[PDB]
Length: 83
Ligand SMILES: [Ca+2]
Image 1 (spheres, protein in one colour):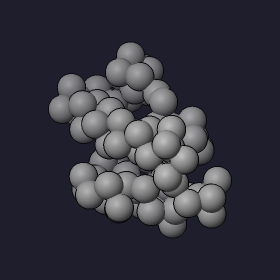
Image 2 (image 1 turned 180 degrees about the vertical axis):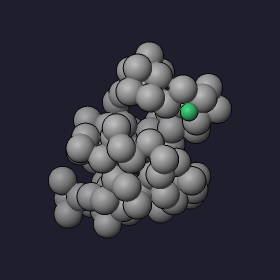
Image 3 (image 1 turned 60 degrees about the horizontal axis):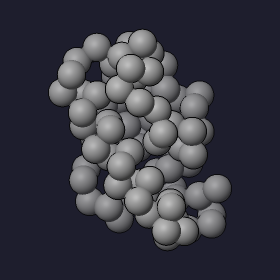
């Protein structure tokens, strides 16, 4: 889950359904699996709700995970193999 090493694992970033499963959020794979991680992590609360993530808790958990990935990305600390 909120192990930064798991969240930023290139294997998981390149497999969003499994990335979501690691957080127990795979039920939203239907709406999110098409979105590459580089785009996915910047989605906001409003967009997540509009895409079917209706539960406040779920949006908060996604946005927390996203934030961790963004931090590594913006420091150029995500392995280039993920891109
Ligand atoms: Ca929901």
